[PDB]
């Protein structure tokens, strides 16, 4: 039963590194990523310039599910796909669940619980890929909610 | 009539820059690129590590046509898509032509004819994105054939 692995964590939590190393050590897995698609369709404009519009986001979402479906419908060599996004939004996670249940695939979770102080340190050294402190703060809160930790 | 713009040229010919600036000045256009997809599915492994296998290339091709179709089937705001690849291979160009003729779309060509000496200079300053001299040489020959220029 092919797997759909969702990485869960704020930017800077180690998701991309894990995904890259996992695929290298586990033949048969492929990566699917929202940031890659957003940058691609805009021909690699400066990250800060990307405007999260309903039109673009819908296109990016469409690319993710169609790619997942095309790959998962592969041969026996295909073991699964990795959705290397933050996946902090409950609605997005539910989408992948209903998607997998519809085609007989198994959804797994790869959690990257990293301390706030550490996330800030890493985020402060990513330049163009860095995220504004307020946005990071908000994603960290969503992560705590996912973990079932208390939040204000 | 929505358009499918194919960029034609060797790496270093200015394709990506043109695509980025064109999309910024022409609302309604979106970028589709083989290199972006190849890097994405492999979780951004080192470029030199990518092995052009039949399995991976087929997946990447599938992502291109499905994305093009999903985007082009958009609203009236969608003016077209840009296939920012080298497109030096006659068979790939024919594929996009039959594809467009099948769904009532128009294919256009954006040629980047750059002198060999210049291509070498630019390629020598791209590091990780640089291409081995022998491969560049071969793509330059294919470009000349496309232009209808004599080759040995």
Image (cartoon, coloured by chain):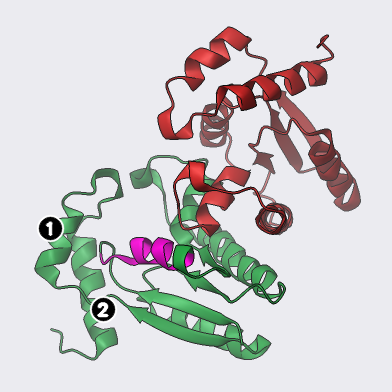
Chain colours: A red, B green
The vertical placement of B54 against A144, above or below, is below
Question: For the residues carrying marks 1 and 2, which lies nearer the camera in this image?
Answer: 1
Among numbered discs 1 and 2, the one appearing first in the sequence: 1
Of A135 and B149, which appears nearest the observer?
A135
Is residue B123 inside the magenta stretch?
A: no
Give the structural element (helix, strand or loop) at label 2.
helix
Viewer-proximal residue among A28 and B44? B44
Q: Quadrant of the N terminus of chain B?
A: bottom right
- Residue A115 image offset from top left, x and y in percent: 63, 9
Q: Residue at x 84, y 44 (%)?
A: A95
Residue A111 visible:
no
SS assignment at label 1: helix
Q: Is A115 above or below relative to A12?
A: above
Inter-mark Cα distance, 1 to 2: 17 Å
Q: Quadrant of residue B19?
A: bottom left
Q: Residue at x 37, y 79 (%)?
A: B110
Q: Which residue is mark 2?
A: B143
Q: Chain of mark 2?
A: B
- Magenta region: B13-23
- In this figure, which residue is indicated by the disc labeled 1? B121
């Amino acid at each position: 039963m092919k797997k759909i692995i969702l990485t869960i964590g704020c930017p800077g939590s180690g998701k991309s590194t894990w995904a890259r190393e996992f695929i290298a050590k586990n033949p048969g897995f492929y990566n699917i990523n929202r940031d890659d698609y957003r940058q691609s369709i805009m021909a690699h404009e400066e990250r800060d310039e990307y405007k999260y519009t309903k039109k673009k986001e819908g296109i990016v979402t469409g690319m993710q599910f169609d790619t997942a479906k095309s790959i998962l419908y592969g041969g026996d060599s295909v073991k699964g796909v990795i959705i290397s996004d933050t996946n902090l939004n409950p609605e997005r996670r539910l989408a992948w669940e209903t998607f997998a249940k519809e085609y007989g695939w198994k959804v797994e979770h790869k959690v990257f619980d990293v301390p706030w102080t550490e996330l800030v340190k890493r985020n402060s050294k990513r330049g163009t890929k860095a995220v504004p402190i307020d946005v990071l703060r908000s994603m960290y809160k969503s992560m705590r909610e996912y973990l079932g930790l208390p939040v204000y």
